[PDB]
Image (cartoon, coloured by chain):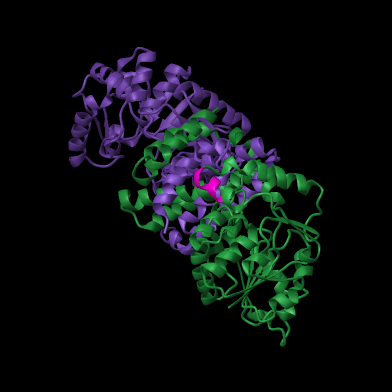
Chain colours: A purple, B green
C-alpha cells in the first residue's frame, strides 16, 4: 500500500516549547537498530514507524521546502541521544533546543525553511516537491499542513489526483469537520468521486517523536477504513485510539485536562451508583445528565470567572461527602481538599 | 416574625439508612443549654435553631399527625446521646436505629404515624392540626411534605390563606420549579395575589439533625426575600448557601459527587489557564464548554455504561499530562491513576 506523506514538518516549535524530547523516536530506533531514526520528528518519525514497524514499504514525502532551505542539523550524534534518553533526556535536550532556537532565529517559516536532524532521504523515502505526483496511486495520504486558511489552497491543488477510496488523514492543525468540508467542496465530479474518500485523523496528540500514540477520528471514513488505520497505528505508534471526530479537540487540545477530570468523575460516579446502590445505568445517566448540563449552563450564564460568586464551592462539601464510597472514594477526597481551600 | 412549619417529619427513614446521627442537634443543645434539642430531627431540629439562635419569637408546627399516632420514644435520655456524640456517635446510634426500626415496622406511615424523641410542645412550639390556621399571618412558611402528587392537594387547601409577599419554602421532596408551578395555578386571582409570593427552599442537604447547613434556591423569590432567608439560615444552621434553583438537585441529590468533581475540575482548569498561561478567562471558558458538552453528548449518545467502548480512558493519559501544571496539578495525578486502571 502506497503512503504519501504531505508535509515534513519543522522542529522549531518543538524546541521553542522547552518540554519535548525524542523518547519515542529513540524507542523505535532501537527496536529496528537504526540509530538515525532517533532524531526524526513529526511526519518523518511516523513514516519510519509505518515503514519499519508496520510493513509499509512504499513511502513518499512531499513538501515544497525540500527545494528551498531544508536544513539538517548534524551537530549531535544519534548514539549520544539514544544513550541520554535511557536515563534522563534532559542531559541532552537543553543544548539541542539552544542550537535549534539559534538556527530558527534567522530561518524563514515553513514552506521556505524547515529544521531536521535526519534527512528523510536517508530512510529510503522517495522525496518530492510535487504533491500531485506524491498522491498518484496513494492509498494512505497523511497531511501535515500549517494552521488556518492555506489548507484548502494546498489541497485543491491535488484533490483530483487522489484515487477513489483512499484514506486521507489530518493532524493537529485542523479540526476533522473543517478538513472534511474541503473535500466536500468537490462532491459532484464523476471522474474523481471524492465522495468515496475515507477522511479521518492520524493525530499524535503530542509531538510524535516524544510519544507513541495516535488518535483516529470516527464519523467520516468507513468502518473498514478506520479498522485499517487503527491496526496500522497500533503497530506503528504502539498505542492507538479510535474515537468520534467530535471528541478529537476535547481529548487532544489543551482542554484535555478538563475532559480527563470529568470523564474520571463520570466513570467513578457511575460505578459507585451501579455497584453499590444496585441501580440500572440509566438511573446514574439521568442524574449525571442534569449535573453536567447545569454546571456547564452556570459557567455560560455568569462566566467561568464568576462561578464562585454564584455557587460557593463549599456548598458541595456537605452533600457530596455522603457519596464518598465505592469508585468515587478514589477521587472525592482530593476534590474535598480543593473545594475546602476555595470556599467563601 | 411568624414561622409556620408545615410537616413535622418522621424519624423512620433516617434510622433505616443506618448512616445518620444527631451531631448538629447536639451542637445547638449545648449552645443554648436545652438538652432536649439533642434528639430533635428534621423540621423540629431546624425550628429550634430559628427560635433559639435567629430570634424567631413565634413558631407553629402544623401536621395532621398530631391527632393520630405521634409516637415519642423516651427510651434514651438526651444525656447519653449528647455524651456519645462528643466522643463517638456509634456507641449509641445502633440501638437507636434498632428501637426505631422495631417500633417502625408496625407503625403507619406519615400522616398517620410519625416517630420522634422530643415533642415540639416541650420546645415552646404551638402545635396544630390545621394548615390554614398555622399559616394565618405567617411570614415564613416552611413546608416539609412527602414526595409525590399530594403536594398540590396539600397546598391547595391553604394557598388562599398565605399572606401576600410571604416566604414559602420547600426541602428535598420537590424541585423548586415543580413547587413553583403549584402556586402558578392561582396566578389570575386579584384577592389571593399569589403572584406576590417569595417561593424558595430551606433544604438541609442531609438530615437536619446531623449537619448544620441549608440551601436556598434563587430564581423565583425577590432579592431581599432571599437575602433575609440567608441571614436567618446563616445563624440558624451554621452554614448557608444560596444558589440557582437549577443547581439545587445537582448539588443536594445523589449526583452531588459528580457536581463536586466537575466543579473542582472547572475551577482548577480555569485557574491554571489564567494564572499560568496568562490568557483571559474567556479563553478557558471557550475550551471548557466544548469539553463539557462533548463528554456529555457522548454519554447521552452511547449510554453511561458504554463510554469506555467508544472512548478509551487511556486516551487521556498522553494528552492531559501536558496540562499537569498550576491548580490542575492538584487534581490531575489522582485522575491519572483512575484512567490508568480503566484503560483498554
The quarter of the picture where the C terminus of chain B appears is top right
The residue that appears at 41% across and 44% down in the rendered structure is A254
Is residue A185 among what the camera can see? no
Which sits in the foreground, B91 or A200? B91
Q: Which of the 4 quarters of the picture holds residue B325?
A: top left
Give above or below for B98 relative to A211: below
A215 in the magenta segment: no
The quarter of the picture where the N terminus of chain B appears is bottom right
Give above or below for B9 relative to A49: below
In this picture, residue A251 sits left or right of residue B273 = right
In this picture, residue B181 sits left or right of residue A48 = right
Q: Main secondary structure of the magenta part?
A: helix
Numbered range of the magenta stretch: B82-87
The residue that appears at 30% across and 16% down in the rendered structure is A35
Which sits in the foreground, A222 or B330? B330
Q: Position of residue A262 (x, y in %)?
A: 51, 44
Q: Which of the 4 quarters of the picture holds residue A151?
A: top left
In this picture, residue A311 sits left or right of residue A104 = right
The residue that appears at 59% across and 59% down in the rendered structure is B37
B86 in the magenta segment: yes
Q: Position of residue A51 (x, y in %)?
A: 43, 19
Q: Position of residue A252 (x, y in %)?
A: 45, 40
Is residue B261 among what the camera can see? yes
Amino acid at each position: 500500500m502506497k503512503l504519501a506523506i504531505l508535509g515534513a514538518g519543522c522542529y522549531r516549535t518543538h524546541a521553542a516549547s522547552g518540554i519535548t524530547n525524542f523518547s519515542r523516536a529513540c524507542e523505535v530506533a532501537e527496536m529496528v537498530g537504526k540509530p538515525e531514526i532517533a532524531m526524526t520528528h513529526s511526519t518523518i518519525t511516523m513514516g519510519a514507524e509505518l515503514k519499519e514497524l508496520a510493513g509499509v514499504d512504499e513511502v513518499v514525502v512531499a513538501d515544497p521546502v525540500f527545494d528551498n532551505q531544508f536544513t539538517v542539523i548534524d551537530d549531535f550524534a544519534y548514539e549520544d541521544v539514544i544513550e541520554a534518553h535511557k536515563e534522563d533526556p534532559e542531559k541532552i535536550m537543553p543544548q539541542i533546543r539552544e542550537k535549534v532556537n539559534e538556527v530558527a532565529k534567522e530561518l524563514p517559516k515553513p514552506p521556505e525553511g524547515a529544521i531536521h536532524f535526519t534527512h528523510p532521504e536517508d530512510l529510503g523515502f522517495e522525496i518530492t516537491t510535487d504533491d500531485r505526483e506524491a498522491v498518484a496511486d496513494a492509498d494512505f495520504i497523511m497531511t501535515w499542513f500549517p494552521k488556518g486558511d492555506m489548507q484548502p489552497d494546498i489541497i485543491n491543488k491535488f484533490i483530483d489526483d487522489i484515487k477513489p477510496g483512499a484514506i486521507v488523514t489530518h493532524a493537529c492543525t485542523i479540526p476533522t469537520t473543517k478538513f472534511y468540508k474541503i473535500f466536500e467542496q468537490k462532491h459532484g465530479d464523476l471522474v474523481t468521486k471524492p465522495e468515496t474518500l475515507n477522511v479521518t485523523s492520524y493525530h499524535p496528540g503530542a509531538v510524535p517523536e516524544m510519544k507513541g500514540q495516535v488518535y483516529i477520528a470516527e464519523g467520516y471514513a468507513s468502518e473498514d477504513a478506520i479498522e485499517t488505520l487503527f491496526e496500522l497505528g497500533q503497530k506503528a505508534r504502539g498505542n492507538a485510539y479510535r474515537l468520534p471526530a467530535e471528541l478529537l479537540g476535547p481529548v487532544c487540545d489543551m482542554c484535555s485536562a478538563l475532559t480527563a477530570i470529568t470523564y474520571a468523575g463520570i466513570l467513578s460516579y457511575r460505578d459507585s451508583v451501579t455497584q453499590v446502590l444496585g441501580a440500572p445505568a440509566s438511573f446514574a445517566q439521568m442524574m449525571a445528565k442534569e449535573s453536567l448540563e447545569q454546571i456547564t449552563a452556570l459557567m455560560e450564564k455568569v462566566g467561568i470567572d464568576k462561578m464562585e460568586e454564584n455557587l460557593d464551592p463549599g456548598a458541595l462539601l456537605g452533600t457530596a461527602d455522603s457519596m464518598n464510597f465505592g469508585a468515587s472514594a478514589e477521587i472525592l477526597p482530593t476534590v474535598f481538599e480543593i473545594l475546602e481551600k476555595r470556599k467563601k
